[PDB]
Image (cartoon, helix red, strand yellow):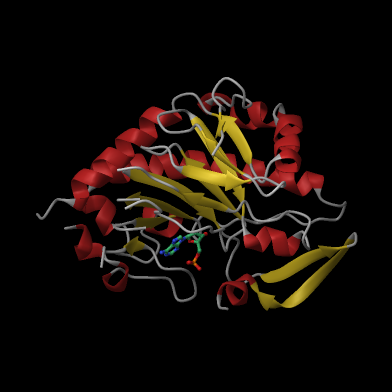
Amino acid sequence: VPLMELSGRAPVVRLHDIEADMAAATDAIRSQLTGWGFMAAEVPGIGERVEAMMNEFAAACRATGSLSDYAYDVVPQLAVGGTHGFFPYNPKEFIHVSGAMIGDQPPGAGDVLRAFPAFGTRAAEVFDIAFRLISLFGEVVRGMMPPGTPELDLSHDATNLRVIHYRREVLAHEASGIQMLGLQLPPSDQGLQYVLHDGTWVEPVIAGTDVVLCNIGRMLTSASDGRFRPSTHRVHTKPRLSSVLFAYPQHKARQWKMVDGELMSLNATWGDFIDS
Ligand SMILES: Nc1ncnc2c1ncn2[C@H]1C[C@H](O)[C@@H](COP(=O)(O)O)O1
């Protein structure tokens, strides 16, 4: 599977200059979505923050003073919404850090980030940078879409940072996101690959880099009435951590499509979109 070098080549977007640096990368990013399934940006300093987060997640996975004390089924959820907290092994381990969890929105939901406060501080930092980046990546996609295209309205409380441990050859079968957009963050190991428009595979060179990928999710495919296919991807590995931000709109908001240039408010909510 051909390797795709990105560090040195993707637009550069600086932590202290995100709004400006993303405006200046609009043209590049559009051409990526058009040329590849997906989009890419180099964010100098993101690598160090993501490696430190992931390393502290691993440590916490083996700690027993335990993450499973905050398994999804014992953490307060929101009435309507997705499910945040730790998902035990029996993606192998994995945690979902929502914006609600960061703000103790269901009071008691941020208790994992208080039990493991070093991973929590780093995960809250990574969430905030990744949400800013993903919302500006979505304004680029909206600008490639017909006039009248509404704002994506990505919700901070519904967005989740997934951090995975242990993800013997194929670690994923080909998959895409349910949600509007994903931000892939530089993983520990190489293996994540994307399908191109020609139906061939590339392996982004992203392990141990400052490169983030942005993924089209099936909600956006639906709202763009087919014009943007999901950024379908898989993971191959050779005898291990990873994290990705899944941006959702508010569950209770009405779905919408741009069909041949016309905006159509639908009956079903984005909530209903997930419940298949
Ligand atoms: N085992 C497992 N559980 C959950 N999500 C996974 C898993 N493997 C891959 N994914 C990812 C990839 C997609 O966005 C998304 C599907 O949402 P979903 O919540 O699955 O409808 O979750």
Position of residue 53 measured from the top left corner of the image (x, y, whole percent):
32, 39
Q: Which residue is found at the position 62% from the left and 73% from the top? A: 273
32 above or below 75? above
Q: Which residue is found at the position 46% from the left and 68% from the top? A: 82
Judging depth in this view, the residue of 184 and 101 nearest the camera is 184
Position of residue 54 measured from the top left corner of the image (x, y, whole percent):
32, 41
Q: Is residue 113 left or right of residue 99?
A: left
Judging depth in this view, the residue of 143 and 20 nearest the camera is 143
Residue at the farthest top position:
8
28 above or below 104? above
Q: Which residue is found at the position 19% from the left and 64% from the top? A: 69
Q: Is residue 222 left or right of residue 238?
A: right
Q: Which residue is found at the position 49% from the left and 24% from the top? A: 44
Q: Is residue 268 left or right of residue 42?
A: right
Where does the C terminus fall, quadrant-wise? bottom right
Where does the N terminus fall, quadrant-wise? top right
Position of residue 203 measured from the top left corner of the image (x, y, whole percent):
53, 38
Position of residue 239 measured from the top left corner of the image (x, y, whole percent):
29, 43
